[PDB]
């Protein structure tokens, strides 16, 4: 499948794409305001993620640091990034379907729209000002709004037992972004698409 990744923010993001134990395509790129990066993802990719990183400095070997979403200091991500990160999540060609969602389960850094560019399903967007509205205890100094599991590391926030309910903190993400996952056991907002669809991820879909 192809994914076009568009930076519509007025500031530079460093896009990242990773299946957790491997880069997808080049794995990361600088995107200035207005730039698009088209990547190819192997059909049958399970648990792929795309996200944006803010305030990054890299050297000439592509080692450095980002204030949100850093993946152990590399330009080209292999691991997932450090919260807070808004996440475009996908599993492709799972018994003839593609599954897509946006997740706030690891916090929120940049607003995002995640849509097919082919027919047969609709997209999802989380474009609210979550950083601006963010509860005081969830605010990440770097910019961004952390999830409660990242901040507090409890069984309840993290559903480490596999049982957990919504919380004050999850209710906040959900109230601003009803279509994003707000905690591990949220009623799914997964969208099912035809096997082998193509997609666009747009940062700051609304700027």
Image (cartoon, grey):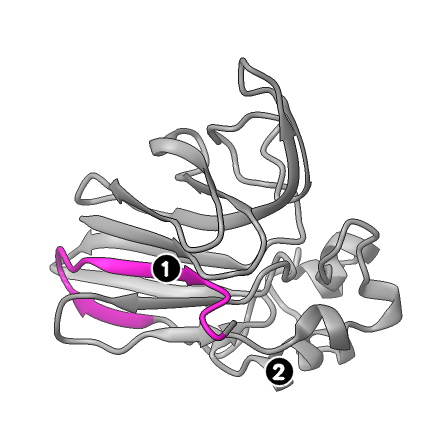
Compared to 105, does 17 lie above or below? above
Name which residue lies at 30% across and 68% down. Answer: 115
Q: Position of residue 129 (x, y in %)?
A: 65, 76
* Total count of labels: 2
Q: Which residues are magenta?
A: 191-206
Picture residue at 20% right of the left edge, 45% below the top:
44
* Contact? badges 2 and 1 (CB < 8 Å): no
Mark 1: secondary structure: strand
User: With respect to residue 83, does 177 lie above or below?
Assistant: below
Give the left or right position of residue 186, taking residue 202 as reference: right
Disc 2 versus disc 1: nearer the observer: 1
- 170 is higher (above) or lower (below) than 143: below
Residue beneath disc 1: 201
Q: Can you tell which quarter of the image residue 28 is in? A: top left
Q: Residues within 10 Å of mark 2 (few under 14, many from 20)?
A: some
**Image quarter of residue 157:** bottom right
Q: Is residue 73 visible?
A: yes
Task: Left or right? Give the position of 179 relative to 48.
Answer: right
């Amino acid at each position: 499948a192809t994914f076009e990744i568009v930076n519509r923010c007025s500031y530079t993001v460093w896009a990242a794409a990773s299946k957790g134990d491997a880069a997808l395509d080049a794995g990361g790129r600088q995107l200035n305001s207005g730039e698009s990066w088209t990547i190819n993802v192997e059909p049958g990719t399970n648990g792929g993620k795309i996200w944006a990183r803010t305030d990054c400095y890299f050297d000439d070997s592509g080692s450095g640091i980002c204030k949100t979403g850093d993946c152990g200091g590399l330009l080209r991500c292999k691991r997932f990034g450090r919260p807070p990160t808004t996440l475009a999540e996908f599993s492709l060609n799972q018994y003839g379907k593609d599954y897509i969602d946006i997740s706030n389960i690891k916090g929120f850094n940049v607003p995002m729209n995640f849509s097919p560019t082919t027919r047969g399903c609709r997209g999802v967007r989380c474009a609210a000002d979550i950083v601006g509205q963010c509860p005081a205890k969830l605010k990440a100094p770097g910019g961004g709004c952390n999830d409660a599991c990242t901040v507090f590391q409890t069984s309840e926030y993290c559903c480490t037992t596999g049982k957990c309910g919504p919380t004050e903190y999850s209710r906040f993400f959900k109230r601003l972004c009803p279509d994003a996952f707000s905690y591990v056991l949220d009623k799914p907002t997964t969208v099912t698409c035809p096997g082998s669809s193509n997609y666009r991820v747009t940062f700051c879909p609304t700027a």
